[PDB]
Length: 30
Image (tube, rainbow, N blue to C red):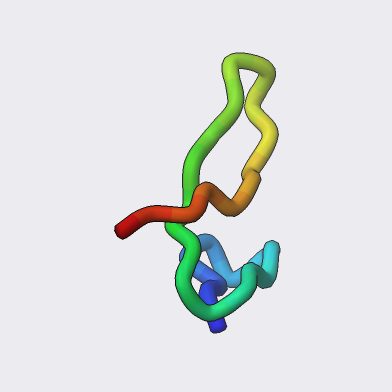
């Protein structure tokens, strides 16, 4: 999976992206 900051997990296939309000979310890429 995707931990990145080791504080938020993400589905295998998404990248760690920070929101304009400091919110870690998974963004799908290809």
